[PDB]
Image (cartoon, rainbow, N blue to C red):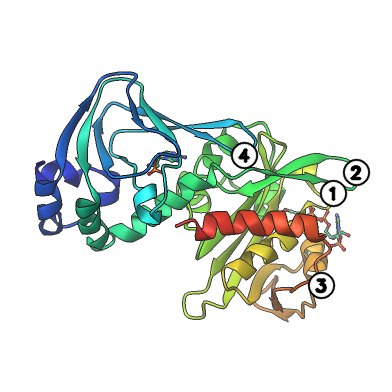
Amino acid sequence: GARVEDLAGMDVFQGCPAEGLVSLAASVQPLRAAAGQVLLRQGEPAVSFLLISSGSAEVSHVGDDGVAIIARALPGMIVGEIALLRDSPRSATVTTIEPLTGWTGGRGAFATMVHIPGVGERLLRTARQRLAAFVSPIPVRLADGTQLMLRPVLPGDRERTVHGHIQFSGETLYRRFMSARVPSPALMHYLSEVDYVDHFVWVVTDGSDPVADARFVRDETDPTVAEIAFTVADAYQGRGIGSFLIGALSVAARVDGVERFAARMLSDNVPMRTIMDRYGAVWQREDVGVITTMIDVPGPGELSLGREMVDQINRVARQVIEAV
Ligand SMILES: CC(=O)SCCNC(=O)CCNC(=O)[C@H](O)C(C)(C)COP(=O)(O)OP(=O)(O)OC[C@H]1O[C@@H](n2cnc3c(N)ncnc32)[C@H](O)[C@@H]1OP(=O)(O)O
Ligand SMILES: Nc1ncnc2c1ncn2[C@@H]1O[C@@H]2COP(=O)(O)O[C@H]2[C@H]1O
């Protein structure tokens, strides 16, 4: 098999004490593939997973719309884990780009891997982030006629925004973060790389570039409550996006077992206060210049969204949340 050292470098194994990797390392087998070799095919039954040492691969998923969604598998990453988590067929076709080496294992070695402390949770989180990219974005039409799309957040949204053309002003950032400075890389990682269970995020785009986001973060002590936050790009404000997003967030919260939303905001934020007032918010003074509220996540019919839109949002939330 491999050396414990050889596994120690894989993403999913970071921080894992050597001892826990012993049998796994002994049980995996070496793999070498040439360039342009198909490793896995979408829809096929599953046996093995692969830990990539070197080289890389294209990942290609054909969705219901018939469009192939493309991604990359890189050195340090596992591939073929999702089918083994779900007992499903392969979610994607995986083809080597350049020559690739690594280690493979079967369902037996996979069982060892998932019981390695901390690892099962990492596998699930990464699987969710991956499957999130295969969700069909939901068309949303604003009152003013603007056509946008609604989808779960993706780790890649950090890069898209930072290098994008959509502007978030100093004022917008202060209203959102209590600082006008551009959000640090560390913060942007935190905002875009999430588990969807405890921390859930919707992104609205123009069909390419993100223009807004909404998130809830489940409270540690009381799982039935979550803290919420919203951001909308300046040019996109005042068009109904925020009002839409609180509804979408409420749909996802229902799937996630979240009964109540908590919020804090500057006392001067009129648009946000108004959005929450619709849902029955009563305001407490928290710090100086900050106010807070708790509201019940609105149930059936008291959302202005309409059934078709509600069902689409519910279907997508479940796809990311419940996939594995
Ligand atoms: C809990 C936290 O998230 S606090 C921090 C929130 N984030 C920020 O403040 C950052 C900068 N601003 C924004 O991101 C956005 O403006 C948000 C999230 C505050 C609001 O979203 P928007 O898309 O602009 O709001 P939207 O157009 O849906 O209208 C909001 C509501 O207030 C009203 N409104 C719209 N513009 C304004 C305005 N300039 N001033 C006061 N009220 C307004 C609308 O009537 C609407 O009411 P409705 O729910 O009955 O339809
Ligand atoms: N968005 C993605 N990014 C990177 N790898 C992915 C992505 N989606 C799927 N995969 C990998 O492609 C594999 C195809 O088979 P599985 O569904 O077993 O497990 C899948 C993941 O390992």
Q: Quadrant of residue 291?
A: bottom right
Q: Going by the image, does 191 lie left or right of 2? A: right
- Residue 224 lies, with reference to residue 129, above or below; the image says below
Give how far apart the Cα atoms at labels 3 and 4 are. 39 Å
The residue labelled by disc 1 is: 239
Mark 2 or 3, which is nearer the eye? 2
Circle number at residue 64: 4
- Quadrant, the N terminus: top left
Q: Is mark 2 within 8 Å of ligand 1?
A: no
Report the residue marked by disc 3: 277
Q: Residue furthest right?
A: 144
Label 3 element class: helix
Mark 3 and mark 1: Cα distance apart in space: 18 Å
Q: Which residue is mark 2?
A: 144
Q: Position of residue 43 (x, y in %)?
A: 45, 39
Residues packed near mark 4 inside 10 Å, few (<14), some (14 to 19) or many (20 plus):
few
Q: Earlier in the sequence, mark 2 or mark 3?
A: 2
Q: Amino acid at mark 2?
A: Asp
Q: Secondary structure at mark 4?
A: loop
| Residue, far front | 45
Q: Which comes before the other along the chain, label 3 or label 4?
A: 4
First-in-chain label (1 vs 4): 4
